[PDB]
Image (tube, coloured by chain):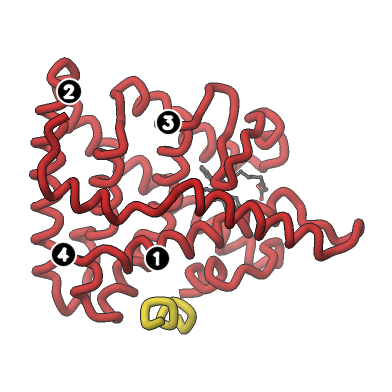
Chain colours: A red, B yellow
């Protein structure tokens, strides 16, 4: 594989997935083990704790990128507030592409779960969102979506051109153009059989964003109705 | 947004 130098630098920012998976699994096990039989976290409550912990990993990933670090905290907050849910969904989708089997759901804790089991515990909204995500998983697997392209899409999601009120919007513009050019060069060069792959990759970002917008609004209102157990970071991202 | 600000400063 011929990898643009920029993409190699982007990959250095990826967390140690095996270690992240273990740490979140121990946290969720200590959570259930620290309460009795009557107050055990519901499946929904566990997913909230899971997403909450994933958000910590996302924040630490962003702050590990040099480009992100050149921005002041106000700018960093504005970028992360605009895309945290999209990053969560994109991460979940990629996880199904890699460690995924059709009919199953692979979680950030490394647990493999049957799709129909989880789906039957969700309402109409999350069922529709989960099913739409699975359709994206299938489309991306057929395109041979790989880790190099994944990291590129993550940076394109983080450094969005639609975030307003930034001090250093120029840095955000420059990152978007650089990653776009690197991703195009990488995809066209490593997947010549899948022509228009690059265009099909970018066409999926608006779908992933739409899914994550609905998911965020659902959680926000579930929290207002008191259905969301306390998850500091997740709650705080919603209450903004 | 206090906790996110702390995470990015820590
Ligand atoms: C958006 C998240 C989330 C966060 C909290 C609760 C739920 C979801 C994620 C994204 C990555 C993970 O951290 C989450 C798990 C995953 C699948 C959710 C299935 C659980 C539904 C049963 C409880 C339903 C009860 C109800 O209906 O209220 C999520 C996901 C993945 C793809 C599309 C949409 C959501």
| Residue marked by disc 3 | A97
| Residue marked by disc 2 | A191
Q: Chain of mark 4?
A: A
Quadrant hosting residue A201: top left
User: Which mark, by number, is residue A41?
Assistant: none
Q: Is residue A133 left or right of residue A223?
A: left
Residue visible at 44% across and 82% down in the picture: B6
Q: Is residue A107 left or right of residue A155?
A: right
Badge 3: how crowded within 10 Å, few (<14), some, or many (20+)? many
- Which of the two labelled residues, at mark 2 and mark 1, occupies the earlier sequence position? 1
**How far apart in space, not on screen, are marks 1 and 4 (Cα)?**
19 Å
Q: Position of residue A23 (x, y in %)?
A: 58, 57
- Which of the two labelled residues, at mark 1 and mark 4, occupies the earlier sequence position? 1
Q: Secondary structure at mark 1?
A: helix
Q: Secondary structure at mark 2?
A: loop
A43 or A37, nearer to the observer: A37
Q: Position of residue A37 (x, y in %)?
A: 91, 56
Q: Mark 3 CB in 8 Å range of ligand 1?
A: no
Q: Secondary structure at mark 4?
A: helix
Closer to the eye: label 1 or 4: 1
- Which of the two labelled residues, at mark 2 and mark 3, occupies the earlier sequence position? 3
**How far apart in space, not on screen, are marks 1 and 3 (Cα)?**
23 Å
**The N terminus of chain A, quarter of image:** top left
- Which of the two labelled residues, at mark 3 and mark 4, occupies the earlier sequence position? 3
């Amino acid at each position: 594989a011929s990898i643009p130098h920029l993409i190699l630098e982007l990959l250095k920012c990826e967390p140690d997935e095996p270690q992240v998976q273990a740490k979140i699994m121990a946290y969720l096990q200590q959570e259930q083990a620290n309460r009795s039989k009557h107050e055990k976290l519901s499946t929904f409550g566990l997913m909230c704790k899971m997403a909450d912990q994933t958000l910590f990993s996302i924040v630490e990933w962003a702050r590990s990128s040099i480009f992100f670090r050149e921005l002041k905290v106000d700018d960093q907050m504005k970028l992360l507030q605009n895309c945290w849910s999209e990053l969560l969904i994109l991460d979940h989708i990629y996880r199904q592409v890699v460690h995924g089997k059709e009919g199953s759901i692979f979680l950030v804790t490394g647990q493999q779960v049957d799709y129909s089991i989880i789906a039957s515990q969700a309402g109409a909204t999350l069922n529709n969102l989960m099913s739409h995500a699975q359709e994206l998983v299938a489309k991306l697997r057929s395109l041979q979506f790989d880790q190099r392209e994944f990291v590129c899409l993550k940076f394109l999601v983080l450094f969005s051109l639609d975030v307003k009120n930034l001090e250093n919007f120029q840095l955000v513009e420059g990152v978007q153009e650089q990653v776009n050019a690197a991703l195009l060069d990488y995809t066209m060069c490593n997947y010549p059989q899948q022509t228009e792959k690059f265009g099909q990759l970018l066409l999926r970002l608006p779908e992933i964003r739409a899914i994550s917008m609905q998911a965020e609004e659902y959680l926000y209102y579930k929290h207002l109705n008191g259905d969301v157990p306390y998850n500091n970071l997740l709650i705080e991202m919603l209450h903004a | 947004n206090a906790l996110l600000r702390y995470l990015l400063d820590k």
